[PDB]
Amino acid sequence: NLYFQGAVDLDREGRDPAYVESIVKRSQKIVDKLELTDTVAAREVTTIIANRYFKLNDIYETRDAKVKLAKETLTGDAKQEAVKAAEAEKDAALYRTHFAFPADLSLYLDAKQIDAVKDGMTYGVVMVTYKATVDMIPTLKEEEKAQIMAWLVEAREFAMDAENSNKKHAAFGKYKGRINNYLSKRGYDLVKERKAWYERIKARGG
Amino acid sequence: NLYFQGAVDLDREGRDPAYVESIVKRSQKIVDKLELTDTVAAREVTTIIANRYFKLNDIYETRDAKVKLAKETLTGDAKQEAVKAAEAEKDAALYRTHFAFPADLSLYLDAKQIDAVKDGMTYGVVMVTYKATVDMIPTLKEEEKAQIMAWLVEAREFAMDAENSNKKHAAFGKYKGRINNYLSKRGYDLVKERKAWYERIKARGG
Ligand SMILES: [Cl-]
Ligand SMILES: [Cl-]
């Protein structure tokens, strides 16, 4: 499956060609899982995803340059304030660019397909985590399931903008922590549920 | 239709009661247009919307205090840099809180209803603008319509977070400018289309 640009320009200029190729291949792999039937649309979506990876890269490079300058020049509270300001500026750049991404995708993809792109950019952690949680506690109430999914989908919106795998898993981890705490406050004995789950996994040949 | 809090706490503490009442009434009016059939869900959604108005208010109050301090203490480039930093910090606060809002709404509302809330918070400018544009140029291509709608929906995502009516209309205005420029670059004679549209409006008794 050889990628070629379509109408959407690939933001390749001035970038290391091996990096560009790695991002395009990553992006192609996400698009493959959509099983699109319009080969031109598939190229366009590939480019849109790649360009978003590249722009995120640039945002984080900017942030890192500011933090490097702070490490070299500042200490104590002044240093922490400069790091805080760089992080706010990073989150601002994410805000300013976040909505254009599904806007652009929507020219080619429906809502379900756009969600599948989000999942592709975030290792499908939403459904892995949701399925595991309901496997662990099969009598969760519908409202508990709904809240758990809502938090995972929120986590995904942040994770898709994160810098790398480590930071993506940290974003999910925050909301997994929230889920854990939520269930314990709602009266579930998580030690007991988890122990019984492991027994069920063994009993079914997992 | 008297509002009463449900399970979601209204973020009322320390706020002027007339302001609280005004925001609750605004929020109730948005929810009324959803025509929900679960009266408890309607109260919860009312509270969620009101609480988002209140949090946006607080974000803008923070931003304004920083800009006031800059006006009182700084001039020239230093002043512009402090204003820039306050705006980045504001956009950061918007980013950090934006995704929780539809997450919370999703416990009560489907995707279509959530969009109707977004429209309610933004004076329905998306559909007014879209309908007017297709009325003005009825032979737009499907891809042009799609791009126009995508830009209006993007505009809405920013507008729903804006401070007031003036700033909401400015957010839409940016993307209306983009639409105007887009159509002229795609070969439409906007002077001619607009003139012929006005004739059609007159001919139909508008
Ligand atoms: Cl190419
Ligand atoms: Cl109340």
Image (spheres, coloured by chain):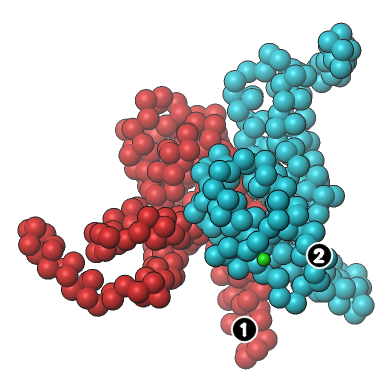
Chain colours: A red, B cyan
The residue at the point 60 percent across, 68 percent down is B9
Q: Please indicate, yes or no, whether residue A172 appears anywhere in the rendered image.
A: yes
In this view, B20 is above or below A153: below
Q: Quadrant of residue B34?
A: top right
Q: Which residue is mark 1?
A: A80
Which quadrant of the figure contains the C terminus of chain B?
top right
**Badge 2 amino acid:** Tyr
The chain that hosts pointer 2 is: B
Check disc 2 and report the residue beneath it.
B19
Q: Secondary structure at mark 2?
A: helix
Name the one closer to the observer, A84 or B206.
Answer: B206
Q: Position of residue A63 (x, y in %)?
A: 59, 67
Residue at the limit of the structure toward the bottom, as seen here: A76
Q: Circle 1 sits in a helix, a strand or a loop, which is it?
A: helix
User: Camera-side residue: A80 or A138?
Assistant: A138
- Pointer 1 chain: A
> Where on the picture, by quarter, is residue A186?
bottom left
Nearer-the-camera pick, A123 or A76:
A123
Q: Position of residue A51 (x, y in %)?
A: 52, 45
Q: Is residue B145 left or right of residue A3?
A: right
Q: Amino acid at mark 1?
A: Gln
Q: Position of residue A42 (x, y in %)?
A: 42, 32
Disc 1 under 8 Å from ligand 2? The reply is no
Is label 1 or label 2 in front? 2
Q: Are marks 1 and 2 on the same chain?
A: no
Mark 1 touches mark 2? (CB < 8 Å)? no
Q: Residues within 10 Å of mark 2 (few under 14, many from 20)?
A: few
